[PDB]
Image (tube, rainbow over all chains, first blue to last red):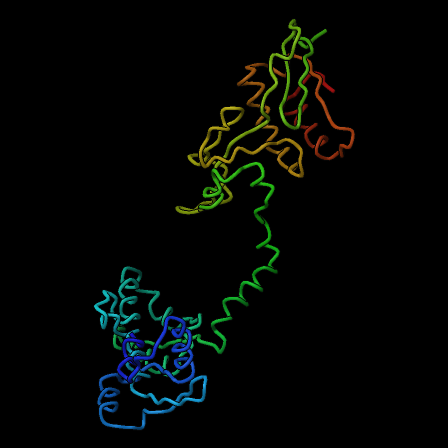
Length: 188
Length: 140
């Protein structure tokens, strides 16, 4: 979608190998939109969004509305016609399949990790969009650390130390006898 | 010489077990030392602890035909770093004796086999078993 955007920015001048580089501009300068309708009203009316970027042989470009426009599709996969709602809404539905008691507890216990979770404007949008879903009287915990991306790697590095965790390391020696034919019932 | 019945041999091999019967001239059997139990680990529902009451909760089979059993992991009480299931070896042999051989260990006599490098405890705990569970008249 963001590629399908900035072709509009005169780019008869784009490649396969540069999604990896759009992604860079994004990681440098994109942010999660805060108030999308009014974000668009502002984008339609202010130059203040617009900021420069630079290209390998000594070439500037400038960008600013695209920089939140594509960063709304998380709340609107429905932009493409994707059946997903805005994702925490889409998700909140499956939570509705469940116990009532949990709900303030899990609101007071929500946890974030992976690369793209780490964008600016995220939580200060999201809590207020999750607020658009929820029942009344909630209080929240948004466990979204710096390097939350790597926090999942580092938690496996701790887990590995647990003596309890070691207590059925699955060997080549099982497999040497077993072959493949029921490893999926050494699994559940 | 006998209890009511004379001695017999089992050679308790760490691949296959072998044996025959009083009057024969061969091992009638040389057979897989193997047994199959589900260990697919989704331990769930209707929970209970600390109560050895009448069961609906066991799913197990023994011998060569236990090799066919699905999700049942056909383990081997052969000796191969696995040694601890000398616990199961009792119940296993109780099947063998009373249910495959279809025999009576308090009436016969016995001879059974061990490696040179054997430790005591695994045998000697089974000695109460040999003379209180199996309650044999004599063995070595």
